[PDB]
Image (cartoon, coloured by chain):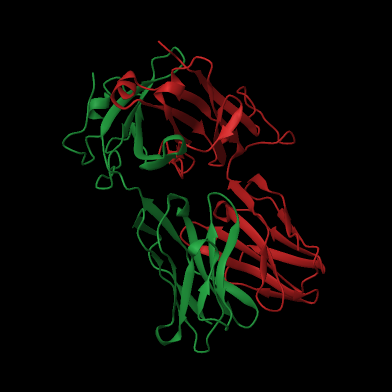
Amino acid sequence: AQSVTQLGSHVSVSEGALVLLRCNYSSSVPPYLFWYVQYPNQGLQLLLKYTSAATLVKGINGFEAEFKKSETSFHLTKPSAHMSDAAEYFCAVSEQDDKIIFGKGTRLHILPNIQNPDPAVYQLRDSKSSDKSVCLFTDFDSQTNVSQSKDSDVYITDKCVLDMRSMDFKSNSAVAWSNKSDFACANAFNNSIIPEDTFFPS
Amino acid sequence: ADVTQTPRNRITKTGKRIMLECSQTKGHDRMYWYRQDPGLGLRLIYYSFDVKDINKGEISDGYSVSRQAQAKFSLSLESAIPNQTALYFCATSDESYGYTFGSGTRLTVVEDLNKVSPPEVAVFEPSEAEISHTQKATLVCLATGFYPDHVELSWWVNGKEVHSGVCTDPQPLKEQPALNDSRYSLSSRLRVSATFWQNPRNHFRCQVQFYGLSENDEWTQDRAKPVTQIVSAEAWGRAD
């Protein structure tokens, strides 16, 4: 088998929804096919493979994939997306009777089901006695995304999802900070489209 | 086999010959070296079917290999350059594509060792406004001023490593994005119940493992030698 194609370096799925990661190959004789997973930042683990036996192959954890030669596909599915499914997935194919060649990989992002969003911008102080601080934008749902800073002295992180197991509670957040003395948390996220009911305490 | 690779982490200057070693115990004929880079998957560098046989993969330029025994397959960067910075994986296979991968070699090639720098680390304490509004409390760790981008951040509550309630940025950002040798920074959050934060018995530590210079390396500057090290910051719970 001369190639394997995954499209979308990053893809999203709603928490609880069908997982579907697409893989297609080019090889006139049916090949062996493999799906590998990689956690940050860890090695590769085999999920499942097609080895010319069952066309529906089942893997660990509810994963399965159907080999379909008539549309040269081997799509990976799982019935319900859990937060622990966040990882990078690689499709791979046999080639030249002597090796495995890897697709470029897709990272799966699971969007938490946030039933009671409570968007807010908080100021946090350094535990030591500078008064350095950072701004924390948190508790917004899936319709919000955070934009890059448009000022080279202000730093803004990508949104990150944490899962507090103690309370079975997930939330989004991004962090902003700057050394500039005119920097205020009220203005930190002005380049992002934030929810109209974002809480801004004093 | 137990496939094993050495070294596990290494930082080097440009221009050096660098050797990575894969070893196996099961004696499979076929061994392989791959590199992994973001957006490109795992690309084959070189592979070998027995002790008499070496063949190029798609990205063999800049590399050589030796198969000195059934059990061993060595990769060399002949003259290291920065674009050889990557995660490297060796693998073995049986005769039916049963692959075994080694656990990885993270290699960072830097132009100028003078620019290596450990992080400064700070913990930022939960807002009273968050505690009041949500009855939850979010700590933020910030690591800054580090180079190269080769760190591992963890959180420690009362001396045990915690994974629940944590989110760490997946990649650091550049402090000076217009510079090729910009320092980096990274943030992480740990969220607990307000209850837990309000207990002055509880101890919270953000730990950053930095990979840098070894004892071997020469160091000519007045500032601290930027050797591989751990840098932490801490906060105690607070009722007031």
A18 on left or right of B58 = left
Does any portion of residue B117 appear in the rendered image?
no
In this rendering, position of residue A197 left or right of residue B156: left
Rendered view: B175 above or below B35: above
**A160, A154: nearer the viewer:** A160
A35 vs A187, left or right, is right
Chain A appears what colour? Answer: green
Q: Horizontal placement of A124 versus A142: left or right?
A: right
Which chain identifier belongs to the red chain? B
User: Considering only vertical position in the picture, is A165 above or below A201?
Assistant: below
Where does residue A120 sit, x and y in percent of width and height? 26, 31
Q: How many labels does the image show?
A: 0
What residue appears at the point 67 percent right and 72 percent down from the top-left corner?
B98
- Could you say which quadrant of the image residue A115 lies in? top left
Q: Residue at x 57, y 83 (%)?
A: A53
Q: Where does residue B74 sit, x and y in percent of width and height?
A: 75, 61
Viewer-closest of A39 and B43: A39
User: B224 or A166, which is in the foreground?
Assistant: A166
Q: Which residue is drawn at 24% across and 47% down?
A: A143
